Image: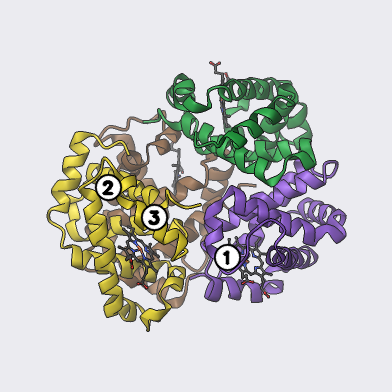
Chain colours: A purple, B brown, C yellow, D green
Amino acid sequence: VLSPADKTNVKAAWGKVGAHAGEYGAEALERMFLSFPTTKTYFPHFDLSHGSAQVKGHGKKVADALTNAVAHVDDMPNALSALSDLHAHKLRVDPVNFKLLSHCLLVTLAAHLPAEFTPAVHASLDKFLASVSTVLTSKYR
Amino acid sequence: VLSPADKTNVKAAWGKVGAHAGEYGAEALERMFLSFPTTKTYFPHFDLSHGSAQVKGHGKKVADALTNAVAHVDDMPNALSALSDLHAHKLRVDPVNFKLLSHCLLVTLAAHLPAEFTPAVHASLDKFLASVSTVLTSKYR
Amino acid sequence: MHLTPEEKSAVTALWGKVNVDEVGGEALGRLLVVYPWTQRFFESFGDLSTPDAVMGNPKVKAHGKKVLGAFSDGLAHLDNLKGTFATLSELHCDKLHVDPENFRLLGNVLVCVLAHHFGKEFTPPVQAAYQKVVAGVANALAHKYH
Amino acid sequence: MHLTPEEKSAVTALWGKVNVDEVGGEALGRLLVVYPWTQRFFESFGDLSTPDAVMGNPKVKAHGKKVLGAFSDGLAHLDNLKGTFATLSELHCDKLHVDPENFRLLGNVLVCVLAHHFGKEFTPPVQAAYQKVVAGVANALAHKYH
Ligand code: HEM
Ligand code: HEM
Ligand code: HEM
Ligand code: HEM
């Protein structure tokens, strides 16, 4: 469960992300596709080459859903019920992959926010991505 | 979440286990130790030879805890609270290990309940063991 | 894939008693019922909404038989799983777009199905051998992914 | 390893700029803070109740340097990780009783620390080569478990 310190930590870090959220979403996806090629099986309809417009646009959507989760940190299941339905009944992405994207998001954050990515903040962000993942896979069966 | 039908399936399958719980627990553990040897690292103080008394004794403890969760299927986080504290603060078993033991429990039940281990029941049992595992791991950080 | 000689005789001994047609349908069917998200690959199979719809679906049974026929054939080549499954690996990656985690889920379900059919005969040591075999097969089916 | 020459050289060139003392201390310390259950092997290191106490703990720091030192020497045996880390695999299993899953967690933490340190230079292709190294090392460290 997210403690008060975690929520504060997550709000602060994401606040600094600010207008780069979309750029960081896209970079996290690109790192995921390269590092964990099995994840490409879910995007056979995308052009997955460097700088493709599909990856960029998708990076923005992912980043925006996270902004929304951070803003609704105390009420995630409700704020993300629609995305949760989407993943469980249409996309049907195997749960193992959420860990892979989460890790790539952390690496992206670490790479772009050196001063803000302290040990305690690293801990909170990992817990937060794990809760988001839990929520997005809660209706799978 | 467990559904009404899941709960019924689990009470029915566990009811047939009855006074075999202990034995099935010890068999689940032996299966785990042999198929996934990395799990032995948590039991360096046990004798792990076939028929070991420590294994039998521990098998019974595991089985009784499962029996208690079945008896309190609508209030599992509270019924398993103490066990949840123990695993998080003292034992500190890595979460991946829970899936390994769950699988071996299912193999054990399948091996012993040929008539009750239908597809629907298998599905409900798997969801049940995953919820138990989630509870036991809920306070890790 | 470290199968000791005695592990390999255990695996082959048991496999000799399997009806692959029947076990193939049960394993594929149970995969789709226990891990419903795997149904994403089978929308052309028709009705998969309830357990009996899935378990008795003639397309699920015919597909299970095909999957397990190829698996058996692999048990005749335990020293060269990678080579044996190379063209299937490529096909699953490039044409079908199947996340290799699905091969691991199927392996585990196959183990429960074997346990279900054989009872006591599926001893802890026999299970341990089969766990190495299903992991070896999953790894071989994934090796051509890129 | 299945490392490509451009990958091999991406790993090596970056590694030549790494301060092993600082990175080791930071990797092990982050591991204990992000995944607190890993503290179970280090009760005798002292106070680990808070991130500040973990990161400032001199035994955490010294152990981090030792672990990364051994990892460092392993980067010169990429064509033979298994043989380089064999005695270490045995020790981790037989004397220390360390669940190999811990090696995976450290690998991922280590990758996050490299990114934190090198920023722009830790590009997606460079990350991919390191992810392969870190899994390779984890697998070599787990190979002698029984
Ligand atoms: C951090 C957790 C994730 C979040 C917050 C997230 C969020 C989203 C959002 C907002 C959409 C767009 C829905 C729309 O168009 O309105 C989406 C779609 C999608 N996501 Fe998830 N996602 C996550 C993880 C994953 C993972 C791990 C995968 C698989 C590797 C994945 C695969 C997909 C796919 C294939 C689509 C549809 C893409 C398209 O056709 O445009 N997602 N996700
Ligand atoms: C289905 C999930 C599990 C349940 C219900 C369960 C239940 C229990 C129970 C009832 C105890 C006895 C504590 C006492 O003395 O009161 C225990 C202890 C213990 N468990 Fe868990 N357990 C589970 C999974 C695991 C797994 C996956 C591991 C690691 C592989 C593990 C490792 C241990 C260890 C090392 C002890 C202490 C044994 C001893 O020193 O006597 N458990 N567990
Ligand atoms: C033991 C592992 C498996 C083996 C040996 C295996 C083997 C095969 C074979 C022989 C075919 C027919 C190839 C062709 O049409 O040319 C096939 C097709 C297929 N397989 Fe796999 N398979 C395995 C696991 C899986 C799993 C776990 C999934 C997904 C959950 C899957 C999804 C598919 C799909 C969608 C097809 C095409 C079906 C169609 O004709 O529309 N397979 N597989
Ligand atoms: C990159 C992976 C790792 C490598 C290369 C590595 C290497 C080493 C080395 C060289 C030693 C010294 C052994 C000796 O004195 O002969 C050691 C000790 C030890 N390692 Fe690892 N290690 C790794 C990961 C881990 C992790 C993840 C854990 C647990 C979280 C761990 C737990 C230990 C422990 C408990 C000791 C004994 C420390 C003591 O003497 O108090 N190691 N390791």
Residue D17, percent from left and from top: 74, 26
Quadrant of ligand 2 in image: top left
Q: Nearer the viewer, mark 3 or mark 2?
A: 3
Q: Is mark 1 within 8 Å of ligand 1?
A: yes
Residue at screen point 20% across, 48% down: C76
Q: Which residue is mark 2?
A: C130
Q: Residue furthest bottom?
A: C47
Residue at screen point 38% across, 74% down: B8
Q: CA distance from mark 3 to mark 2?
A: 21 Å
Tell me the kind of residue under disc 1.
Phe
Q: Which residue is mark 1?
A: A43
Q: Quadrant of the N terminus of chain A?
A: bottom right
Q: Secondary structure at mark 2?
A: helix
Tell me the kind of residue under disc 2.
Tyr
Q: Nearer the viewer, mark 2 or mark 1?
A: 1
Q: CA distance from mark 3 to mark 1?
A: 18 Å
Q: Which residue is mark 3?
A: C89
